[PDB]
Amino acid sequence: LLREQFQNPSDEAKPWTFWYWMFGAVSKEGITADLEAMKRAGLGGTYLMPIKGIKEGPQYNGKAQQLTPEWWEMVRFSMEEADRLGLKLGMHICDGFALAGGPWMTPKESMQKIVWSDTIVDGGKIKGLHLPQPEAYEGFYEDISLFALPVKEEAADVMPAQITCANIATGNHIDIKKTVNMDDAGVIRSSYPCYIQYEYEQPFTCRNIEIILSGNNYQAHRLKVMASDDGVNYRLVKQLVPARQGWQNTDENSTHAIPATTARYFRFYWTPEGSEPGSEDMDAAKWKPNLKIKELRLHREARLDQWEGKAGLVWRVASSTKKEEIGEQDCYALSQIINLTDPFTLTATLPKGKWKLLRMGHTATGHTNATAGGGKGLECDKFNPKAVRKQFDNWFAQAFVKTNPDVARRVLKYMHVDSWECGSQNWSDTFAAEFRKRRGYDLMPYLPLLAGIPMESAERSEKILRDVRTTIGELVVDVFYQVLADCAKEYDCQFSAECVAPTMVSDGLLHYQKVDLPMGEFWLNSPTHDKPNDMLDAISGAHIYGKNIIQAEGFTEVRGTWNEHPGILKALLDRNYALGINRLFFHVYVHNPWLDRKPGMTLDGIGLFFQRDQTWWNKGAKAFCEYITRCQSLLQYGHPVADIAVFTGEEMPRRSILPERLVPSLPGIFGAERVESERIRLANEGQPLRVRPVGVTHSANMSDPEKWVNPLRGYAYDSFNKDALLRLAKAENGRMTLPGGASYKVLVLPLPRPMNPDPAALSPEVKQKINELKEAGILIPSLPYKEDDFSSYGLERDLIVPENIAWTHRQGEQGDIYFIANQLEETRTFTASMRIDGRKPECWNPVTGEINADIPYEQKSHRTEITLTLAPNESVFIVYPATGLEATEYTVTFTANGKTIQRQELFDWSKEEDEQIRYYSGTAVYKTTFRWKSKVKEDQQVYLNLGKVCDLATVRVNGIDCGTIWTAPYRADITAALKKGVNELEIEVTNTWANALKGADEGKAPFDGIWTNAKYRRAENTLLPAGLLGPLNFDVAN
Ligand SMILES: C[C@H]1[C@H](O)[C@@H](O)[C@@H](O)c2nnnn21
Ligand SMILES: [Ca+2]
Ligand SMILES: [Ca+2]
Ligand SMILES: [Ca+2]
């Protein structure tokens, strides 16, 4: 019975929280208080992750520094308390929130990259020549190969040049100080159209431009390169193209190839016009459209376009290099290169002429788990099974040894890996052998490709580099993930994992096959830091690899301002349920070690502030968690339904596809109005800015996941990869099926897109599997698909609802479930039509738990239609089996500071003269009486409507609890509690911390004990409305 699960949910259905210990400031008192608070809210467990240590926050006097006996004692006490209370625990595989580092790791055991040095020497009899040492992270380096290259031309790779600049932005409403300029350090800055000019003594032949930045700068990659011989007639060379890039893009410079150009003068023209708005695969374009360049280096030696990325040193995608840029003349044949490893100071004999001595080897990338404290150190080598095992043994395994082994064996059931923040890597000591087994040929002779030196042809080079990247991503799965999965089963743990993309070269779906619990992430009020693409990686991964529980780190808030409460979290949560998550993890519960300070310790103001010292914790968090649990009991039932699978291609890196990127492929499915708004948005005219949250200025045409509810207008889709196609896909009854229950009718092979611009050719195997699926009846539409839907092919929309209604559909042996959620902040009445023929629908309310088994419905064209009224932000589940107030005076007690006042009229606290009410945050108890004339009749239902509630209210009538009201409709069923005559009305109203913190900031604190390390505040500088504002009314229905 689904009803037993909805009314009595199982433990799997409960939401969890991340629990962050800050700066080693931890106490047993606070531990007990936190774990009891979590139990009281109805949480299932917590992930215990310490962040930073004493050194990073000396002011807090921490005594529980990571890995000290005192810290381990606190971990033990937490396990003991979680055992007592019936909570489960997880921990991360390292200290801090990312990723797999620790002080036990040496440079040799860390993430490795290919490095090199060179010198030009005359050939002949070389004896005892000392070659320059390549990059050696903390002295660690190891040679791999030494190559001898014949010199192409004989001139310097770079020459000196006189650098000038000029503003050209005319249309004079301009701030003259923000026009182009070069500072003392040679750094170039501009906000306005301009050019930077380089004048050489003699004509210089340039084939590429290395752009060197100080942090990220989208606009630096948008320069238009021009050249001249005579200083006035300038010819176009190339409009540069930004590579796709994530947020961790500063480990390498960027090389832009150009057609070989010989000139005395080069100009780089810039304008902000034509900028793409920001996204997760052009992270730098989220920021202000200002130009900032540390150095442009113009080079002579041929290099592949955007080679740093193509070599796998950083996560990047760009087009193959054109033949106009790298012709066969520009590439070295294998027979031209002499391999001098064996001789290697160097003593050997080369032919005559001049030779380049490319000394190649490997060193650490230098990445650490930087948010750790006592457990901080180098990131483990991600391709080395032993280093990965070692990392497991030294942190996570130790929680079963250093605490209390029998208690740890019962409560510590979850091992987590968060989202990658340790860059990329492209070598390890097993990498040549792995490449050979997997790709079927030897990489070693082609090692100079990893320096972007072209060999044989531009195409052969880039085909090989793609293979390197493919191997890289395969090894993240087959080593790092495989090893941790084995370790997890060995310790009887479930394995949760977040995204690898867009920081480590990877197929972003691929690793989810190895984990029990794929985990996405969604942010609150943080468009610059939100990760909708991560969400779709985790969901798509779970769906294609058959993982039924999909966790999500939810409500992460880049700057929390203390005005947040469950009411304004609901719509955000509901649209992520619509995407397919079904176990929320709250981000974040911060341990507050002091019982006398509130709201206390935070992650330096990064929200959501989800913890015991919230004004609304005791009643608000519990009510919300009840909603969540009921929602999740049903959203974990059976299998998700999606009719459309979309192939993610054969470029590397790769990941799930965002809805926006499919609009030119399926313009019909999205509709003409979506096509039109995308063209306006992407044209990004004037590069408009928005500030959200306070102090975060960014591109206003950023794709906003709130504007992409139900984007395929009644269908759902998963991204789907080569591995799933080749290893798992089956045709059954006209649909493509996978183990775990995915069944798709349609397979979209998208048009070339930003993340797959070539696009990479389909391998013969893929072509062969696609053809088998065409023949077994699977729709593989011709693109662009221009019809409104797939009903011409007998595939109707699953749910027809109006815009701004989020939904999902699950199906199992006991029937069908549609989750339907209003995203607008208004009451709406609308028809929902479901693809269900001849079964009786019911309406199950996840806020109250009420089940209405007898709703009206029509049956038309073999669908079922229902009329729904949804209050602001209201959600429902559709399940298919297989008169004013006349009150006496109010007594209002403000419990935090004991004030009590009498009032006839309801009032906004923030408008009172008394500063202890004006600035009050917390709970106030309202007490009054009312007359009810008649006895409550049969079939008759009575609601106390609260009107406007700031922000949360618990209703007691004649001492009977009639519920905690936190979202619309703001009303309480008082039917069972009503008596004839005089009724007693008690209402507890709770607001948010914002007003009290504003009071405390200004010396007008409404009570003592107010402190937090969270410093961010709303820009508005206003007191929020607060209280039972009403008006109060009764509603008598049937
Ligand atoms: C706030 C932390 C958060 O706690 C972590 O999940 C980490 O993945 C991250 N990425 N950006 N910001 N964070
Ligand atoms: Ca994360
Ligand atoms: Ca493709
Ligand atoms: Ca794309």
Image (tube, rainbow, N blue to C red):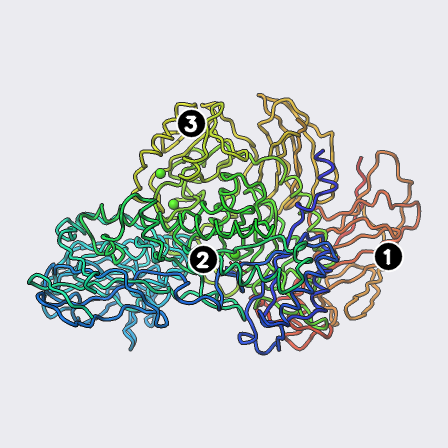
Q: Residues within 10 Å of mark 3 (few under 14, many from 20)?
A: many
Q: Give the spatial CA distance, label 1 vs label 2.
A: 69 Å
**Is 726 placed above or below 699 here?**
above
Instruction: Say which residue appears at 44% left-offset and 48% top-offset.
Output: 477
Callout in the foreground (1, 2): 2
Which residue is located at x 37 percent, y 49 percent? 653
* Image position, residue 923 (x, y; %): 76, 62
> Upstream in the sequence, badge 1 or badge 2?
2
Image quarter for ligand 4: top left
Could one spot residue 671 in this view of the protein?
no
Q: Secondary structure at mark 3?
A: loop
Q: Mark 3 highlights which residue? A: 779
Residue toward you, 881 or 706? 881
Residue position for label 2: 386
Instruction: Please report the residue visible at 84 percent of the width from the left and 34 percent of the height from the top.
Output: 939
Tell me if the residue at label 3 has its CB under 8 Å from ligand 3: no
The quadrant holding residue 769 is: top left
- Three-letter amino acid code of the residue under disc 2: Lys
**Is 659 drawn above or below residue 367 in the view shown?**
above
Image-based side of 640 in relation to 628, left or right: left
Ligand 1 neighbours mark 1 (CB distance < 8 Å): no
Mark 3 or mark 2: which is in front? 2
Q: Position of residue 915 (x, y in %)?
A: 72, 72
Label 2: how many Cα within 10 Å (few below 14, some 14–19, many 20+): some
**Residue holding disc 1:** 928
Q: Nearer the viewer, residue 897 or 319?
A: 319
- In this rendering, the answer to whether 1015 lies above or below 229 is below
Tag 1: residue type? Thr
**Which residue is outermost to the left?**
352
Q: Counting residues from the N terminus, which is met first, the one under dot 1 or under dot 3?
A: 3
User: Residue 174, located in which quarter of the rendered image?
Assistant: bottom left
